Image (cartoon, rainbow, N blue to C red; front, side, top):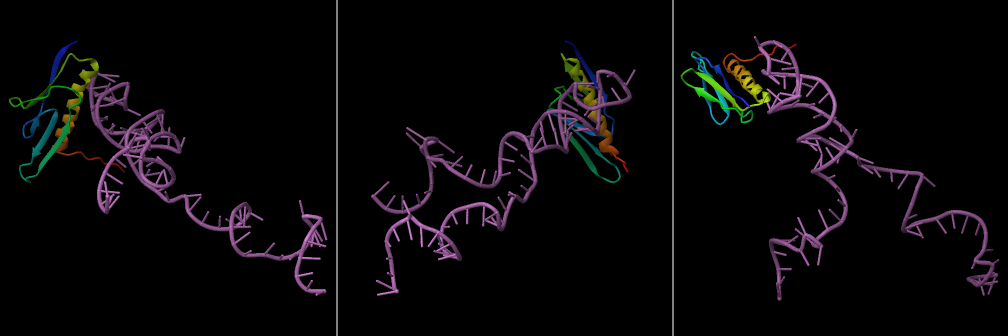
Length: 96
RNA sequence: AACGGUAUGUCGCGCAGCUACGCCGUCUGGGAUAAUGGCUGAAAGCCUCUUAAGCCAGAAGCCCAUCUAGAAAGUGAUGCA
């Protein structure tokens, strides 16, 4: 029984497109010339994603939600923050 | 005597047939689950297997694969009529 939104600033030097709940993050290195691309279907967690070209930010919003559905705003930006570090620098897991 | 009868003759061995006390087969990988263990991750700027979305691993159990029956599941392809 409440109406609100939260935002997240994707930086410069990293392209994205968002359509039908499918977040396609991608990155281009200047020197070595290697594209990288990550895609995830987020049709579940029913939230309105939008990409603001002006602020290069992604905004998500949760109308009329229970406290279970407000968690999904934070879970979106949990995945997307890993996606930006995953495409640019790349995750290693040292184990021995 | 030979070759037979009768005592549903007794003893010895005995193919065929059946039979065990004999002989051969019982291979083999999925899928979704139950308990439970994990990954990423909010709610709760920390932290958590989800007590939230999403993902993985998972029982002699359940469903497939295999095997038995099978179109009054009144079916079908091909020969003639």
